[PDB]
Amino acid sequence: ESADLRALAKHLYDSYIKSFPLTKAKARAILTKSPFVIYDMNSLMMGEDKIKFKEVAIRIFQGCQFRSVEAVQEITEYAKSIPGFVNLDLNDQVTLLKYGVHEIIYTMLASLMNKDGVLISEGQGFMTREFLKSLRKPFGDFMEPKFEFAVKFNALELDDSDLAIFIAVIILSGDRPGLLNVKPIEDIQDNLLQALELQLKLNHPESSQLFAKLLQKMTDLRQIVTEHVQLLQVIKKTETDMSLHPLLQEIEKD
Image (cartoon, rainbow, N blue to C red; front, side):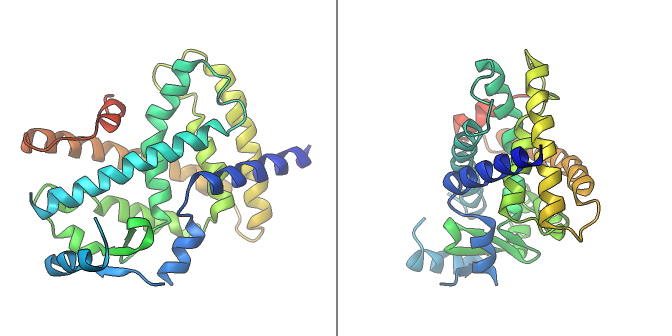
């Protein structure tokens, strides 16, 4: 019954709102109180006279990782609201979050990107794409593929009510390595898929095959994740004096 797929849609959209303070709709309002724009070395030092936040590239990287840690917490809180998620085997909950969290982070980061740059510090700042592309040789391309994905992902013009269902689908992937009870996970994702399909078809009636096109974006995400972790291993051996947050260290071990 369709009425049950709309209730699920509304439920998840409500929890997403409650779980993620910087929504896509607020980010689009900002990008179209305006942000401080960092674009070079000196605007970054200026950026602290107006914003409040050991070499530049490292420090930028550490900020990205700290907001990843913050994002992991919000995604975790959002997952608990997905009906059936908390009744799963505790080890699988951990597995679902372990392999889903990076895919969601870059899904939602696209909401804060345009082709020119990315919102930071809860939207108070805006770091341009080329300044990021210009950092020291390892870090200078840590954000570029995310920009590439974001530009194609944002072409679908999903809004938040769409992303809430989509993010739910990503968490509940039976595909993940080490899952003990694949079946009850898939039974939920199948119901989330049903909710998303009806959601896209109602929210974007003129956007044919958006559902299918959204599902194909699930391959670009996994590529972003992969080159991210290899990039992370290059840093760990190139920067033996730079630490990483253990919540992220524990999650990045696959």
